[PDB]
Amino acid sequence: GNECIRKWLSCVDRKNDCCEGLECWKRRGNKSSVCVPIT
Image (cartoon, rainbow, N blue to C red):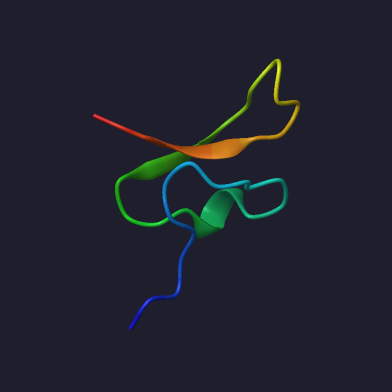
């Protein structure tokens, strides 16, 4: 099924929840870490 945080989503306390292919990246203007696409 689907048990993970999609892309471009807030991951304040869910850094290890980001879906496959994403990483909890901290922002500056947003002030809230979000799952970003990794290479």
